[PDB]
Image (cartoon, rainbow over all chains, first blue to last red; front, side):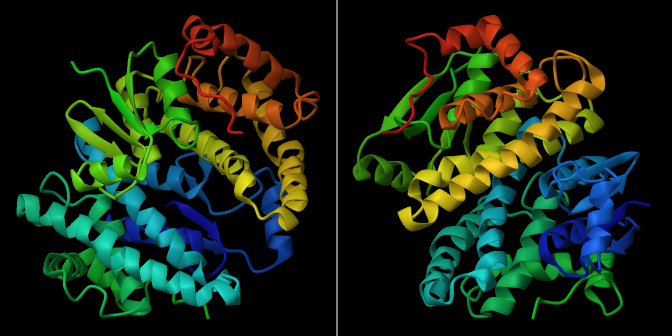
Length: 206
Length: 208
């Protein structure tokens, strides 16, 4: 079992909890509860850049969310079939990451910037991100973003739709194919289960 | 096939790490510079930018945007992403560290001036206490000429590019890391990289 080292919170580890659950992959978590939990992982050499997230998997101690995710997507066959399909997947998910990063940092936003930032994010959701993904779905007519087969792109996007719903639930209203993807993916057995009470899935930061 | 075609401003910014990697791989590419708002508008309006932003690279029939998507495709295409899933994990970890420190340096200019003497000092602390020791430690652990798999990878390249910008910031920062110094000279003397560091290459200058 992969072992996820992090605080008991979403943060930078939640996207990995979603990917591993969507792939049927069981895992353990070990939560950092104090400064001395963290200082101990550092002192043991566990953290190449002194930071978590860190995941122990197949003999490695991987840090950096993108390295963790890339490894797991490839290992569990969620990274498409060849380098061209990786490339679409990578392009789609890096856009998802950029939008995610905005939302994820919004609560540490200086209070005097908050109004402006919220408007800018919703304007990007409506005019930049959601149109791009609706287009992809519409261009090929298929249930999945890439190669007609579940990949990390579907997972990461649907994860983000849930965060956008929490932020403002009207934002997705004009994008039926996104809504439809959300529904379809949220009904896969592994994701439906992760979405039910009792899973490793974490609440919003308060 | 088509030479890859890089669409960006005529500056370093977020395309420079792409220039380094292609030039290191011996790959001939063309550049199409964005000079005006109108130029960027036309790329957008043409539907060439999935997310309405550059960098964008035309390669193998795709219009790839997002720096990490571009880099990841080119590294695999030219055997600069390791030989298997485990070596790529190490490469990804190494290069995401590099990108974190690189982003901080990259943005430092557009810091508001009242915060800039404190950013700069924080950057220098992490270089000396976090990043350079992390990479010196990898190099010392294997004794080999390259970071991963005893073979040129994209990690050596992104790392040595960042060594050049760290030098621009403060040439003293590297002085206690003998293996990083050694890496930088060796990689800089690779034929393709020596050429790219010679005048008249696509390598771009600092911004003024």
